[PDB]
Image (cartoon, rainbow, N blue to C red):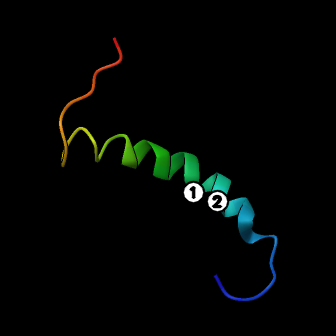
Amino acid sequence: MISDEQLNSLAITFGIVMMTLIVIYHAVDSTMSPKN
């Protein structure tokens, strides 16, 4: 993250991959949340 760029197409790409590691980091670091 340097200048004006369209590279905010990472904050989707990366960010479904960060949303799976955060919600995973909540099962490891914090208390276990199961869905099913």
Instruction: Name the outermost residue toward the top.
Output: 36
Q: Which mark is residue 30?
A: none
- 11 up-or-down from 3: above or below: above
Left or right? Give the position of 35 relative to 16: left
Helix, strand, or loop for circle 2?
Answer: helix
Left or right, 36 with respect to 3, comes to left
Q: Residue at x 32, y 41 (%)?
A: 24
Would you say 7 lies left or right of 24 here?
right
Extreme bottom residue here?
3
Crowding at dot 1, Cα within 10 Å, few <14 / some 14-19 / many 20+, comes out as few
Give the residue pinned by disc 2.
11
Q: Position of residue 14 (x, y in %)?
A: 57, 57
Q: Amino acid at mark 1?
A: Phe
Q: Residue furthest front?
A: 31
Which residue does the image show at 80% across and 78% down from the upper left?
5
Which mark identifies residue 14? 1
**Where is the C terminus found, in terms of image quarters?**
top left
Q: Position of residue 35 (x, y in %)?
A: 35, 17
- Residue shown at the point (75%, 88%) measured from the top left: 3
Q: Position of residue 34 (x, y in %)?
A: 28, 21
Q: Nearer the viewer, mark 1 or mark 2?
A: 2
Asked if 6 appears above or below 13 in the picture, the reply is: below
Q: Is residue 35 above or below residue 3?
A: above
* CB within 8 Å, label 1 to label 2: yes
Label 2 Cα neighbours within 10 Å, binned few <14 / some 14-19 / many ≥20 = few
Q: Amino acid at mark 2?
A: Ala
Tally of numbered tags: 2
Q: CA distance from mark 1 to mark 2?
A: 6 Å
Q: Does residue 6 appear to the left or right of 35 in the view shown?
A: right
Kind of element beneath mark 1: loop
Q: Residue at x 24, y 38 (%)?
A: 27
